Image: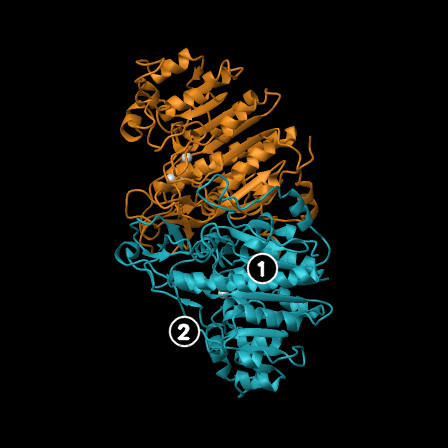
Chain colours: A orange, B cyan
């Protein structure tokens, strides 16, 4: 039912070289914003995270894919916006650590407590805290966790695992790096073992490799984690046909989709940026990655499937969806891979908003875990790092720069960044907020105890 | 009490290492946001521009001066926030130029038309378009133009000069670089000549150097631009005592405060960042500039006086205040200089919000012309550019990196950035908008017919 509006168009309205032609607005917004404010309960929440998707990453993707004056029909369409802070903490001192990793930030919105880089579901004293997904399930809501990364990666793992190091994917790494969590030492187990215990109704992503490990203790000792999932009643799917065939997902038959051995394939291919890449080389045009395929569900397809299965729960549901490789390609100084994964996320955001606008009691939030390296610079820039010129939709060149690491991976950055929302309680993302306020916002919107 | 609320406190509410201790919100914001929405006329508008003040610059300055969980009482206190685009145009092709300079962006919000880099008050066809200040004056409102830069500099110059290159400060520069604008060639003249013609009520800043020049033609041929200003009824002040002695500023008594020959002094000093500076040099604590003075009005002081003098006009006033050297210090890879000028701007914003909250019909907007180079990165970063470690208010180290230029000056960046507002019609900065939308928003809120 239409009541709260989703923005229909914020593209430049006309000829950008003419007076008024670059305007994104067509009239006053006071009434539209009033219509966007409701404090009624959120029956459902869909939280979409672009990993590393700072304002710079949004702008670069929009400039390339949609044109400077273009509009992301998903990402740019949420009417209530603000800027939030995502600093982590130094484990020893408890003081702020100004640049977080994916684990401490996902732990912050999923538990409401700040923590140290690399921690999942625990605070600086390594004490476990319940996550918004575990809380939703406990309250009888359906739950979904979707990501284009390995499911053991920090972002999706924070919702279902409590470990002292994000490296504890399976039994082997846990025994070596998180001895206190190792199952054979009396702990709760590896990230994959804890994910199997958490039992969200719908879990979709990559990361099949770790399921080949076998447990070192417990009821399923000696069996692979895949065998364990099967013995525990999970429906396992591995491709788009398998996924489409699923008709239900619930506690009796939870769904686990493992679509790649490690990360899922990126949407677009292009070369890595290089030293004086914008002065020494010709411009790059991105191209679709052949490895995608009709056999691999897209992030928008996984999102739609999750929504269809979780919406069957009369009480409501919580769903987190992660466009994971925006960050990974930004680390790899690869504009095409980075931008393609941002376009990918925009499609999933559109599916979420289409659902939310019709359902009327769904709060949709779109943001990032932290900012990143990429910068949009003048075409004639002579920079010390890695740069690349790109042919955009506008038929002009845009140059991107990665200038914060001499090491193999570009670095995260600490800038506050955009958080946007639509639906019941969306006012709580406007103005300056902290990433831990998002936990409390989601908890209150759902009316959780 | 002031119906429209100013955010009182969005600092972290407690122990950031404890659950909820880093929250900036104390409860639901739906009602507060409803109370912040009004479409009544803006009687007055105060536009504050932090040149180069992207989200990264706001965050770095907050982290250093207020701590990561701190709160800028001015900058962070506006309740309605969005992200806006500021791309310029390639003059020859008319397509977007993804990274603007100060001239094209200030032309965009002051005229509503996109333009090429370096252009002031003209489009890509070199055609003049009226500025919001010129229009405000024509309508019977009082007008103020305040900046810590030279008054010929792009930001304040865009409100009163129409020239094909921002370099046309005076007669000499104009005759060689903007032959078509040179007075002795029939044009409207240099930036300073046009500024004297525009005759705003209150003009305060630096740039007295150019006034030594003498007109090549016109009624004041042979006289220095300063002699000319005196000759045209201008009330000239040059220090703080002379300025805070002025009791009135109007058309027969326009005020021209020239407080420095070039740019006004920055607040704080520190070493410039250097290669591997966060690794090879000690962390830095910023030092107060001993030559910043007590006979030189601060930005907050110039803002307050301008407000006192412009508010006597019953119809209303338009005032633009620029914290100009955030950008200039970012170009110089100087974190302390940059952060201190951001702190300086925050003080001016507090004065504006305090007045606006009492007055009730004043729209205040805080934003920047474009983004910039500085990035916050991990303490152990090994970057190819210039870096520096800083001792923050939290008693922890923050490292900043400038990595997009091997040249003498760091580069602007193209990322969309925060725009925030308070007062009538503030809803028009929420969500995604363009810098040219801000012109239409100001014009319409004042009801300039
Ligand atoms: Co991340
Ligand atoms: Co991630
Ligand atoms: Co990362
Ligand atoms: Co600028
Ligand atoms: Co400026
Ligand atoms: Co600049």
Earlier sequence position, callout 1 versus callout 2: 1
User: Around disc 1, counting alpha carbons within 10 Å, would you say few (fewer than 14), some (14 to 19), or many (20 or more)?
Assistant: many
Q: Which mark is residue B290?
A: 2
Q: Secondary structure at mark 1?
A: helix
Q: Which mark is residue B190?
A: none
Q: Where's ligand 2: which quadrant?
A: top left
Q: Quadrant of residue A72?
A: top right
Asked if labels 1 and 2 share a chain, the reply is yes
In the picture, measured across the screen, residue B22 lies left or right of residue B377, that is right
Between circles 1 and 2, the one closer to the viewer is 2
Residue located at (60% from left, 72% from top): B305
Q: Secondary structure at mark 2?
A: loop
In the picture, measured across the screen, residue A404 lies left or right of residue A339, that is left
Total numbered circles: 2
Quarter of the image where the N terminus of chain B is located? bottom right
Circle 2 chain: B
Q: CA distance from mark 1 to mark 2?
A: 35 Å
Circle 1 chain: B
Quarter of the image where the C terminus of chain B is located? bottom right
Q: Which residue was labeled with disc 1?
A: B109
Q: Position of residue B443 (x, y in %)?
A: 67, 60
Q: Residue furthest bottom?
A: B222
């Amino acid at each position: 039912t239409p009541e709260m509006p989703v923005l229909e168009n914020r593209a430049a309205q006309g000829d950008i070289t003419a007076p008024g032609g670059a305007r994104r607005l067509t009239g006053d917004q006071t009434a539209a914003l009033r219509d966007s404010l409701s404090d009624k309960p959120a029956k459902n929440i869909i939280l979409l995270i672009g990993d590393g998707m700072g304002d710079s990453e949004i702008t670069a993707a929009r400039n390339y894919a949609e044109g400077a004056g273009g509009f992301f029909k998903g990402i740019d369409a949420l009417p209530l916006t603000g800027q939030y802070t995502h600093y982590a903490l130094n484990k020893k001192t408890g003081k702020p650590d100004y640049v977080t990793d994916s684990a401490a930030s996902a732990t912050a919105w999923s538990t409401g407590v700040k923590t140290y880089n690399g921690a999942l579901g625990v605070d600086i004293h390594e004490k476990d805290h319940p996550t918004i997904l575990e809380m939703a399930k406990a309250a009888g809501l359906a739950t979904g966790n979707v990501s284009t990364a390995e499911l053991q990666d920090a972002t999706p793992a924070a919702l279902v695992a409590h470990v002292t190091s994000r490296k504890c994917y399976g039994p082997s790494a846990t025994s070596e790096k998180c001895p206190g969590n190792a199952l054979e030492k009396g702990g709760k187990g590896s990230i994959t073992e804890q994910l199997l215990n958490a039992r969200a109704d719908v879990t979709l992503g990559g990361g099949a490799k770790t399921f080949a490990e076998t447990a070192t203790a417990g009821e399923w000792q000696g069996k692979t984690l895949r065998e364990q999932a099967q013995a525990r009643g999970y429906q396992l799917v591995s491709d788009a046909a398998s996924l489409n065939s699923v008709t239900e997902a619930n506690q009796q038959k939870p769904l686990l989709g493992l679509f790649a051995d490690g990360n899922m394939p990126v949407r677009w291919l292009g070369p890595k940026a290089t030293y004086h890449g914008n002065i020494d080389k010709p411009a790059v045009t991105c191209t679709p990655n052949p490895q995608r395929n009709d056999s691999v569900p897209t992030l928008a397809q996984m999102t739609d499937k999750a929504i269809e299965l979780l919406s069957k729960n009369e009480k409501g549901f919580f769903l987190q969806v992660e466009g994971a490789s925006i960050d990974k390609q930004d680390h790899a100084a690869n504009p095409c891979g980075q931008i393609g994964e941002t376009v990918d996320l925009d499609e999933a955001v559109q599916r979420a908003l289409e659902f939310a606008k019709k359902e009327g009691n769904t709060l949709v939030i779109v943001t990032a875990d932290h900012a990143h390296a990429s910068q949009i610079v003048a075409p004639d820039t002579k920079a010390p790092g890695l740069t690349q010129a790109l042919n955009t939709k506008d038929g002009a060149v845009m140059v991107m720069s990665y200038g914060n690491s001499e090491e193999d991976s570009q670095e995260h950055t600490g800038s506050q960044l955009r958080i946007a929302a639509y639906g019941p309680h969306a006012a709580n993302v406007v103005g300056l907020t902290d990433q831990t306020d998002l936990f409390y916002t989601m908890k209150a919107a759902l009316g959780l105890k």
